[PDB]
Length: 284
Ligand SMILES: Cc1ccc(C(=O)Nc2ccc(CN3CCN(CCO)CC3)c(C(F)(F)F)c2)cc1C#Cc1cnc(C(N)=O)n1C
Image: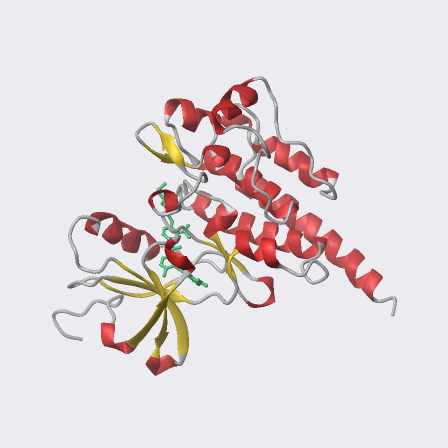
């Protein structure tokens, strides 16, 4: 309506900033409130101060293109002057890994685990359709809201998480146990390497958040996969889910299913499971 208008830019002072979320392990992300709309939000900030600026602007540019119920949805940014903000709606229960690790398993039952897998595969089919590559798909990068809503996110954690999730590899930091063989060896990433990660993410969901490849040194992971060793089916994981899991972990990326195929398979399984569940609960 005026020369300097940008439909994504918000006024920083519209937001009340509160506490840092995730103890620093998720970088500079704060809880906030968009006062005018009575909406609790999460806010990522750069905070002045030279040097990370390009990747912050790239993240904002990417998020302006992503609109899907199971992917985080940009509400606004402040990128005219520092501190920069990227703002999305707050998701009540935080990241999926800690959610699985702290949940009430009578509440988060097999049918809910399938619902969450289904939602994640929906988000990935959307990204695949748009030709985007996630590059770090894992439970720690998924978010949980009310009624077991899941949204895929990305917190650029390689630089931020401490401990052994990420370790030095090809000069950067890789989550070795989520990383496709072609990505570890040849540094090639694609939607098929995301598919491989999705398989590991399915194993996280099935085990309620166990760390992958239990008791195996990160240094032996590539050699094992090369011999065709794969993680075993976790207790209680249905056979059909383990089969999809195994397809995601085919050595040759072109041999992995597409997210369109995966999502179709989950929707089927979830609908099957939902029926069987309404029936069994309808006893009493
Ligand atoms: C404030 C905030 C800002 C940004 C994001 C965010 O997820 N950014 C993002 C950036 C890029 C991409 C896609 N690319 C990945 C890299 N790729 C590299 C290139 O291969 C390109 C494709 C995606 C994706 F994956 F979802 F689409 C998300 C999350 C939050 C949050 C939050 C929040 C909500 N509730 C809570 C809570 N309770 O504590 N918190 C913490």
